[PDB]
Image (cartoon, rainbow, N blue to C red):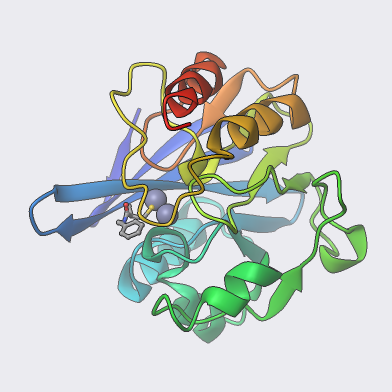
Length: 229
Ligand SMILES: C[C@@H](CS)C(=O)NCc1ccccc1
Ligand SMILES: [Zn+2]
Ligand SMILES: [Zn+2]
Protein backbone atom coordinates (compact mmCIF):
# COMPACT_ATOMS: atom_id res chain seq x y z
CA UNK A 1 0.00 0.00 0.00
CA UNK A 2 0.89 3.68 -0.41
CA UNK A 3 3.04 5.17 2.31
CA UNK A 4 2.54 8.82 3.11
CA UNK A 5 5.85 10.32 4.21
CA UNK A 6 5.55 14.01 4.90
CA UNK A 7 3.99 15.51 1.80
CA UNK A 8 5.19 12.70 -0.51
CA UNK A 9 3.84 9.24 -1.30
CA UNK A 10 5.88 6.08 -1.81
CA UNK A 11 4.65 2.81 -3.34
CA UNK A 12 6.57 -0.44 -3.68
CA UNK A 13 6.30 -1.82 -7.23
CA UNK A 14 8.71 -4.78 -7.07
CA UNK A 15 11.14 -6.24 -4.50
CA UNK A 16 13.80 -3.62 -5.31
CA UNK A 17 11.68 -0.85 -6.94
CA UNK A 18 9.57 1.93 -5.45
CA UNK A 19 7.66 4.85 -6.97
CA UNK A 20 8.05 8.30 -5.42
CA UNK A 21 5.29 10.88 -5.82
CA UNK A 22 5.43 14.60 -5.08
CA UNK A 23 3.00 17.48 -5.65
CA UNK A 24 3.13 21.08 -6.83
CA UNK A 25 0.34 23.62 -7.14
CA UNK A 26 -0.05 24.80 -10.71
CA UNK A 27 -2.38 27.79 -10.21
CA UNK A 28 -5.54 26.96 -12.23
CA UNK A 29 -4.68 23.24 -12.60
CA UNK A 30 -4.58 22.10 -8.93
CA UNK A 31 -1.91 20.16 -7.08
CA UNK A 32 -0.17 18.12 -9.78
CA UNK A 33 1.35 14.76 -8.91
CA UNK A 34 4.64 13.66 -10.44
CA UNK A 35 6.13 10.17 -10.14
CA UNK A 36 9.68 8.91 -10.28
CA UNK A 37 11.51 5.73 -9.25
CA UNK A 38 13.87 4.39 -6.62
CA UNK A 39 15.80 1.18 -7.36
CA UNK A 40 17.95 -0.89 -5.03
CA UNK A 41 20.84 -2.52 -6.90
CA UNK A 42 22.65 -4.68 -4.37
CA UNK A 43 24.34 -2.36 -1.86
CA UNK A 44 23.36 0.91 -3.50
CA UNK A 45 20.30 2.91 -4.52
CA UNK A 46 19.59 4.53 -7.90
CA UNK A 47 17.03 7.32 -8.40
CA UNK A 48 15.04 8.23 -11.51
CA UNK A 49 13.80 11.85 -11.42
CA UNK A 50 13.84 14.36 -8.64
CA UNK A 51 10.71 15.63 -6.92
CA UNK A 52 9.39 19.07 -7.90
CA UNK A 53 11.48 20.88 -5.29
CA UNK A 54 14.76 20.65 -3.41
CA UNK A 55 12.93 20.22 -0.09
CA UNK A 56 10.79 17.39 -1.49
CA UNK A 57 13.87 15.75 -3.00
CA UNK A 58 15.67 15.88 0.35
CA UNK A 59 12.56 14.09 1.71
CA UNK A 60 12.99 11.35 -0.89
CA UNK A 61 16.56 10.92 0.39
CA UNK A 62 15.27 10.83 3.98
CA UNK A 63 12.76 8.11 3.04
CA UNK A 64 15.58 6.15 1.37
CA UNK A 65 17.70 6.45 4.52
CA UNK A 66 14.87 5.15 6.70
CA UNK A 67 13.46 2.43 4.44
CA UNK A 68 16.56 1.18 2.58
CA UNK A 69 19.57 2.61 4.45
CA UNK A 70 22.07 2.28 1.62
CA UNK A 71 23.94 5.00 -0.27
CA UNK A 72 22.39 6.62 -3.32
CA UNK A 73 24.98 6.06 -6.05
CA UNK A 74 23.41 8.14 -8.80
CA UNK A 75 20.31 9.80 -10.15
CA UNK A 76 19.15 10.15 -13.72
CA UNK A 77 16.56 12.78 -14.69
CA UNK A 78 14.35 12.42 -17.72
CA UNK A 79 13.96 16.00 -19.09
CA UNK A 80 14.41 19.65 -18.16
CA UNK A 81 11.07 20.39 -16.52
CA UNK A 82 10.63 21.07 -12.81
CA UNK A 83 8.86 17.84 -11.98
CA UNK A 84 11.91 15.85 -13.14
CA UNK A 85 14.82 18.21 -12.39
CA UNK A 86 13.55 20.68 -9.82
CA UNK A 87 15.46 19.01 -6.98
CA UNK A 88 18.91 18.81 -8.57
CA UNK A 89 20.51 21.01 -5.91
CA UNK A 90 19.31 18.64 -3.16
CA UNK A 91 20.97 15.72 -4.95
CA UNK A 92 24.19 17.68 -5.28
CA UNK A 93 24.09 18.77 -1.64
CA UNK A 94 23.79 15.07 -0.73
CA UNK A 95 26.87 14.15 -2.83
CA UNK A 96 24.93 12.14 -5.40
CA UNK A 97 26.26 11.84 -8.97
CA UNK A 98 23.68 13.16 -11.43
CA UNK A 99 22.99 12.41 -15.08
CA UNK A 100 20.72 13.82 -17.76
CA UNK A 101 20.49 13.85 -21.55
CA UNK A 102 23.08 16.31 -22.85
CA UNK A 103 20.19 18.26 -24.38
CA UNK A 104 18.45 18.46 -20.98
CA UNK A 105 21.63 19.89 -19.47
CA UNK A 106 21.85 22.42 -22.32
CA UNK A 107 18.21 23.44 -21.81
CA UNK A 108 18.35 23.46 -18.02
CA UNK A 109 19.27 27.09 -17.40
CA UNK A 110 16.59 28.51 -19.76
CA UNK A 111 14.03 26.20 -18.16
CA UNK A 112 14.97 27.45 -14.69
CA UNK A 113 16.70 24.17 -13.77
CA UNK A 114 20.14 23.34 -12.44
CA UNK A 115 22.00 21.04 -14.85
CA UNK A 116 23.05 17.55 -13.91
CA UNK A 117 26.77 16.93 -13.43
CA UNK A 118 27.06 14.47 -16.31
CA UNK A 119 25.63 14.33 -19.81
CA UNK A 120 24.23 11.25 -21.47
CA UNK A 121 24.57 10.91 -25.23
CA UNK A 122 22.69 8.52 -27.48
CA UNK A 123 23.33 6.35 -30.49
CA UNK A 124 21.29 6.88 -33.66
CA UNK A 125 19.02 3.98 -32.59
CA UNK A 126 18.21 5.70 -29.28
CA UNK A 127 20.18 3.58 -26.81
CA UNK A 128 22.44 5.49 -24.46
CA UNK A 129 26.13 5.44 -25.32
CA UNK A 130 27.33 3.17 -22.50
CA UNK A 131 30.46 5.16 -21.64
CA UNK A 132 28.22 8.11 -20.68
CA UNK A 133 26.15 6.01 -18.24
CA UNK A 134 28.80 4.30 -16.12
CA UNK A 135 27.66 2.16 -13.18
CA UNK A 136 23.99 2.36 -14.18
CA UNK A 137 23.48 -1.32 -13.19
CA UNK A 138 20.00 -2.43 -14.21
CA UNK A 139 18.97 0.97 -15.58
CA UNK A 140 18.69 0.85 -19.36
CA UNK A 141 18.36 4.37 -20.76
CA UNK A 142 16.69 5.01 -24.12
CA UNK A 143 15.98 8.18 -26.09
CA UNK A 144 12.75 7.42 -27.99
CA UNK A 145 12.72 10.58 -30.10
CA UNK A 146 11.09 13.94 -29.45
CA UNK A 147 7.61 13.82 -27.96
CA UNK A 148 6.56 15.38 -24.68
CA UNK A 149 9.75 17.41 -25.10
CA UNK A 150 12.72 17.31 -27.47
CA UNK A 151 14.95 15.94 -24.71
CA UNK A 152 12.71 13.34 -23.07
CA UNK A 153 14.39 10.05 -22.13
CA UNK A 154 13.07 6.76 -20.76
CA UNK A 155 14.43 4.04 -18.51
CA UNK A 156 13.91 0.30 -18.28
CA UNK A 157 14.83 -1.72 -15.19
CA UNK A 158 16.59 -4.90 -16.22
CA UNK A 159 15.53 -7.96 -14.23
CA UNK A 160 12.05 -6.55 -13.61
CA UNK A 161 8.97 -6.13 -15.72
CA UNK A 162 9.10 -2.33 -15.34
CA UNK A 163 9.80 0.46 -17.79
CA UNK A 164 9.50 4.18 -17.05
CA UNK A 165 8.14 6.49 -19.70
CA UNK A 166 8.36 9.71 -17.70
CA UNK A 167 6.08 12.41 -19.04
CA UNK A 168 5.97 10.86 -22.52
CA UNK A 169 3.38 8.23 -21.56
CA UNK A 170 -0.07 8.60 -19.98
CA UNK A 171 -2.29 5.77 -18.75
CA UNK A 172 -4.81 3.88 -20.80
CA UNK A 173 -7.77 5.88 -19.43
CA UNK A 174 -6.22 9.35 -19.94
CA UNK A 175 -8.26 11.97 -21.81
CA UNK A 176 -5.23 13.99 -23.03
CA UNK A 177 -1.44 14.18 -23.26
CA UNK A 178 -1.31 17.03 -20.70
CA UNK A 179 0.69 20.17 -21.39
CA UNK A 180 2.16 20.06 -24.89
CA UNK A 181 3.84 23.48 -24.63
CA UNK A 182 7.28 22.02 -25.39
CA UNK A 183 6.05 18.99 -27.35
CA UNK A 184 7.02 17.77 -30.80
CA UNK A 185 3.49 17.08 -32.03
CA UNK A 186 4.56 15.60 -35.37
CA UNK A 187 6.86 12.98 -33.85
CA UNK A 188 5.08 12.23 -30.54
CA UNK A 189 3.23 9.11 -31.68
CA UNK A 190 6.34 7.52 -33.18
CA UNK A 191 8.36 8.33 -30.07
CA UNK A 192 5.76 6.73 -27.79
CA UNK A 193 5.81 3.61 -30.00
CA UNK A 194 9.62 3.57 -30.01
CA UNK A 195 9.60 3.52 -26.20
CA UNK A 196 7.37 0.46 -26.30
CA UNK A 197 9.57 -1.25 -28.88
CA UNK A 198 12.73 -0.60 -26.81
CA UNK A 199 11.28 -2.40 -23.76
CA UNK A 200 9.12 -5.11 -25.31
CA UNK A 201 9.05 -7.32 -22.20
CA UNK A 202 7.96 -4.59 -19.80
CA UNK A 203 4.46 -5.36 -18.57
CA UNK A 204 4.33 -2.57 -15.96
CA UNK A 205 4.62 0.91 -17.39
CA UNK A 206 5.42 3.67 -14.90
CA UNK A 207 4.98 7.28 -15.85
CA UNK A 208 5.05 10.75 -14.39
CA UNK A 209 1.41 11.77 -14.35
CA UNK A 210 -0.54 8.54 -14.08
CA UNK A 211 -0.40 5.50 -11.78
CA UNK A 212 1.41 2.40 -13.10
CA UNK A 213 -0.46 0.66 -15.90
CA UNK A 214 -0.22 -2.11 -18.45
CA UNK A 215 1.22 -1.63 -21.93
CA UNK A 216 -2.18 -0.23 -22.93
CA UNK A 217 -0.74 3.05 -21.60
CA UNK A 218 1.70 3.00 -24.55
CA UNK A 219 -0.81 2.05 -27.20
CA UNK A 220 -3.39 4.56 -25.92
CA UNK A 221 -0.82 7.34 -25.66
CA UNK A 222 0.37 6.70 -29.20
CA UNK A 223 -3.19 6.56 -30.52
CA UNK A 224 -4.00 9.92 -28.88
CA UNK A 225 -0.76 11.32 -30.28
CA UNK A 226 -1.84 10.17 -33.77
CA UNK A 227 -4.52 12.96 -33.48
CA UNK A 228 -1.85 15.67 -33.11
CA UNK A 229 -0.62 15.05 -36.67
C1 LIG B 1 3.76 18.84 -15.20
C2 LIG B 1 4.65 19.90 -15.85
C3 LIG B 1 5.94 19.35 -16.44
S1 LIG B 1 5.75 17.94 -17.53
C4 LIG B 1 3.82 20.66 -16.90
O1 LIG B 1 2.90 20.11 -17.52
N1 LIG B 1 4.17 21.95 -17.03
C5 LIG B 1 3.48 22.89 -17.93
C6 LIG B 1 4.21 23.18 -19.10
C7 LIG B 1 4.76 22.16 -19.90
C8 LIG B 1 5.46 22.49 -21.06
C9 LIG B 1 5.64 23.82 -21.44
C10 LIG B 1 5.09 24.83 -20.66
C11 LIG B 1 4.38 24.52 -19.50
ZN1 LIG C 1 7.67 17.83 -18.83
ZN1 LIG D 1 5.81 16.07 -16.19
